[PDB]
Figure 1 (cartoon, each protein chain N blue to C red):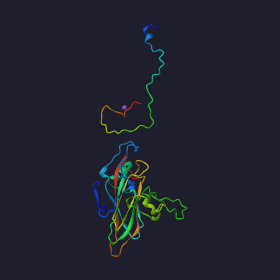
Figure 2: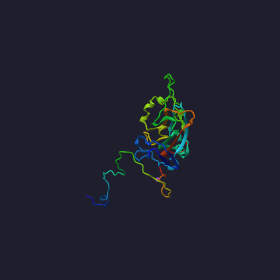
Figure 3: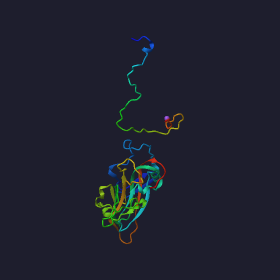
Figure 4: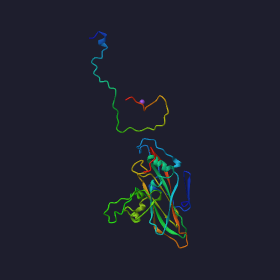
Length: 245
Length: 50
Ligand code: NA
């Protein structure tokens, strides 16, 4: 009754029989922008069911040596479905998200993933190693799209900050002996009421193994991690031609 | 005193500045109201005569 769950939005339904409750980021559900917080004057478009629905975007393989990955929002979805089209045809965008990370193994496998959402996840570089070069991360690294990107130095989250404190952010753990998914609801987080879905990623999703995957030889060795997410309360404004960058 | 009609009905000497406009309080920028589509003849706000 805390372990079983069904999430239905749009024409999509997710089920899980080994859940660990649901986290509502910063204790606040997503909502549409009020007339007093808004500034842009055109009437927005709110497509509803055709964009607020679950999209399964990618699968990674968890290996005994995996470092961890990240995805950026709304970047992961800007080229997918009717949501993508709207994000491309409109200058302004805003929405919340329901994130459902999936990973099942067996009662004989073990390991624990930390699944967290970090708003304004700015990536740093190793500065030429010596720390004397002011190098910058390239586009494919700051906005990896649906493929996500692998962390080079998980301990400092590729940004000079301790992953040990990442739990100060909305998160759940997928500890194999306990659950097989993480569900996080994130409201729209920004210092502006609407923004560009292309130029700005409001938050990053981090999936990092903290207790490494293990099992005895002979047990299924391919343990996938699949990412499914749904935009909530999407609004778009400032219509013109479609743009991808 | 003035006996001829034209002197009586005269506006010579009117010292009141007749103003066509007046100031209104305006501490903030004007708000925007909801609007919908209008497909109508006769009414035409876009057309002007500079
Ligand atoms: Na007019």
